[PDB]
Length: 58
Length: 59
Image (cartoon, rainbow over all chains, first blue to last red):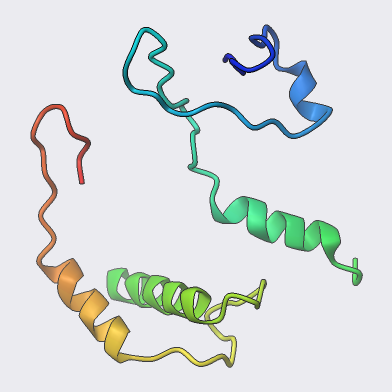
């Protein structure tokens, strides 16, 4: 997995530190990019989970 | 089971796209959802044909 703006990413440990925004899906040129196995499958999970984290009842 | 599930899906989708502010907007939430869009949603699901042509994704 390559960030392609600053540098590529070797391990996955740094994902815990902060949120990351990647480049375009390309689907052309030498940089084929291509979506990951879990690309966009977690749609409602983020919404309700951040709703839980921001809730003041818990 | 399939009709119950699809009804829940349609109600949730219409509810969210019509009432975007609400976060925990669920199937029992008393927020305005309309039934004409739900009926058309069920109608289009009845005649869905997925494209299996190589290249472009299965849509």
